[PDB]
Amino acid sequence: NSSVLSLVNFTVDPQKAYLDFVNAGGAPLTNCVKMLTPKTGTGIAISVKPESTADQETYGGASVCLYCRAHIEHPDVSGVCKYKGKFVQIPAQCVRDPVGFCLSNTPCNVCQYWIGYGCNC
Amino acid sequence: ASADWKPGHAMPSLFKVQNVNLERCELANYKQSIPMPVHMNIAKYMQLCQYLNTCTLAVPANMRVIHFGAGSDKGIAPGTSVLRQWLPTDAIIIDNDLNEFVSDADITLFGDCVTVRVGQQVDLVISDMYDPTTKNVTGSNESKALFFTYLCNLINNNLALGGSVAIKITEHSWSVELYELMGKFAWWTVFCTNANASSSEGFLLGINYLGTIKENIDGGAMHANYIFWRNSTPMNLSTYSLFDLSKFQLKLKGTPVLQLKESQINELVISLLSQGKLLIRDNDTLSVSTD
Ligand SMILES: C[n+]1cn([C@@H]2O[C@H](COP(=O)(O)OP(=O)(O)OP(=O)(O)OC[C@H]3O[C@@H](n4cnc5c(N)ncnc54)[C@H](O)[C@@H]3O)[C@@H](O)[C@H]2O)c2nc(N)[nH]c(=O)c21
Ligand SMILES: Nc1ncnc2c1ncn2[C@@H]1O[C@H](CSCC[C@H](N)C(=O)O)[C@@H](O)[C@H]1O
Ligand SMILES: [Zn+2]
Ligand SMILES: [Zn+2]
């Protein structure tokens, strides 16, 4: 943790820096805050309350945000984090690297499910 | 095994009314851990929340919740996220810790809790604070000051009538003054989660603040009663209560917030306060900053 977190402070593209690190064998960021949930949710990517389906796990949003975890500027032109204060659903097969998954994907702009993991548009 | 499916154990009046010396706490399963599927504090906080689901908590719109001791040595705040999952979506969470962390709170303040200046009154105080030096046990187990001085003043000044508190204590991390302040609530207990049953930890609960003395409590004797209870009560580690979470979220009670002068507080108002049906405090915008 304290290494990959240290790494993404030595680069201009923290998203690419993290992904290249874990794509080359780096240990994913640990200690993401996994919640216990009734697997009866809608399955959207980001939600005010947990929304995991039986195929998903829910995390506290700040804990899966690279920018929150590394204490660096968020890239949102709004300056407001998309995850913090909310909950984020991750496909269950991807719990090994929740942060890597979030950096690697984008919720659907119309249906709010993960593109390729729920979006049916 | 009924109790295994409960979120934990609450101190019964059987032990509240005893009168005994303060003895050493000796738990049979001391420091045994239960495996989690997930940080242990997830299950601890959810069990506390489940028990508070059985209490007459006031649950207004724009509920004001402050969470002290929210950080971990990992830089995250599992308890705050549980509070986010539990509380109404429009609840305001302010959390605080000595050390840096990141959380799903609305407002996060670093530094000693004493630097946390609350301009208004809040509706719910959660404290998980514990000072590392309490581990240096030398001599008598005496009432502690530490952050309890701050919390006691908070209860007396910055807590709405009808508001509640849940404050972590242990065998050695405890305060005579805080126990005595439980006598200013409609009801009080100590709640011990099943997930951490092997610890002398308990959450001292004051339910529905009344601002006036309802029960005269000898705080030193009451801590001796709490330890006598722990020493007398087998508690099996368990998270069975988290197997069914269909009703985990705090009920959306729409509790009203009223402004009232002290002299207007009649018997009707006290009854409503004591039932979780009313809060008395400002309806301004909340201001919680570091000083
Ligand atoms: C109850 N108890 C206390 N002691 C002895 O008395 C000392 C102080 O006792 P305590 O008041 O710390 O209570 P306890 O040991 O039950 O607390 P525990 O470690 O479970 O800590 C509870 C919570 O305090 C906080 N905490 C503990 N340590 C720290 C820390 N170092 N920094 C921040 N928070 C901490 C955490 O939230 C933790 O979950 C113990 O360290 C031990 O020598 C016992 N010894 C035996 N043999 N059997 C016991 O049952 C027993
Ligand atoms: N005086 C004080 N002001 C603010 N935080 C304090 C404090 N004294 C102790 N603490 C905090 O008490 C915390 C106890 S452990 C907190 C665990 C946290 N609730 C979780 O969910 O993991 C420690 O982080 C410690 O820094
Ligand atoms: Zn963020
Ligand atoms: Zn879509």
Image (tube, grey):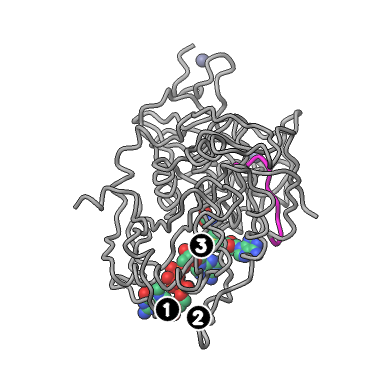
User: Which residue type does callout 1 highlight?
Assistant: Leu
Instruction: Determine if marks 2 and 3 fall on one subunit.
Output: yes
Is B106 a magenta residue? Answer: yes
* Within-10-Å neighbours for mark 1: few <14, some 14–19, many 20+: some
In the rendered image, residue B166, in percent from the top left (x then y), is placed at 51, 53
Instruction: Tell me where residue B16 sits by quadrant.
Output: bottom left
Instruction: Determine if marks 1 and 3 fall on one subunit.
Output: yes
* Nearest to the observer: residue B205 or residue A49: B205
Q: Which residue is identified by label 2?
A: B141
* Nearest to the observer: residue B278 or residue B74: B278
Q: Can I make out residue B73 in this image?
A: no
The residue most toward the left is B1
* Within-10-Å neighbours for mark 2: few <14, some 14–19, many 20+: some
Is residue A58 shown left or right of residue B245?
right
User: Which residue type does callout 2 highlight?
Assistant: Asn
For disc 1, the chain is B
For disc 2, the chain is B
Q: Which residue is identified by label 3?
A: B216
User: Which residue type does callout 3 highlight?
Assistant: Asn
Stretch in magenta: B104-112
Is residue A51 shown left or right of residue B151?
left
Residue at 45% in and 32% down = B251
Q: Which tag, 2 or 3, sits closer to the chain's start?
A: 2
In the rendered image, residue B284, in percent from the top left (x then y), is placed at 74, 33
